[PDB]
Image (cartoon, rainbow over all chains, first blue to last red; front, side, top):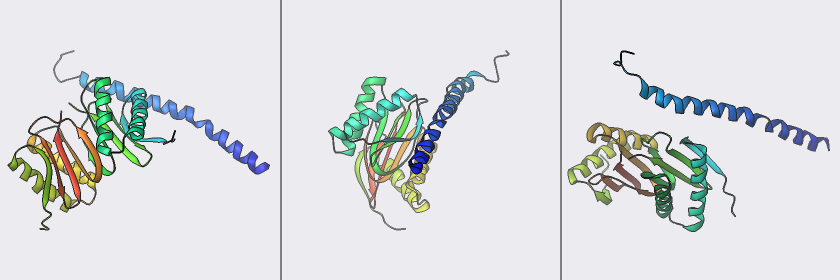
Length: 48
Length: 89
Length: 89
């Protein structure tokens, strides 16, 4: 009984991390999709 | 339905198109048995869907290094079959 | 030089271009032990020589169906190693 309890507790504890993993995924996307445009943006000319 | 879990081994992608790739590659593998023909089916179906042109390979032992269009590159595993698909052109 | 006879299956490109592919592919196979690095070598040296964008696939079994611009397609065997090199970009 307590071994099954350990297993269930460990599994549900594991389940918490996916939210923060998705958070870092969102960070990945925000970096890449914006950085493509940002690298295409600037140049030596354009006296702005 | 044989639950061949997808492990996507690289992608410069959005997620919806990756899952479309997984689903349709599973459909092709269920429908055909020739790796060349699997890649052919997947390549035509994406060429129809998200506008040409891609390049798709289906196989077990193969290594690749190509240049692709941004947000248009996937490479995953279904069962024992590695499937790469990148848009360039 | 181990005379790995380049039995060439599919080809839409010139014979000197074929021979350049075959020579530097012997070069890539004799220099590298990983098929991914071999393909990276060949694609990079074709990008240097015959301009981007090349796509090289080195493997022992795989299914390929790609769109290539004309005069830029090779698919041959060095020993048991299948090599598919095509330009698309």
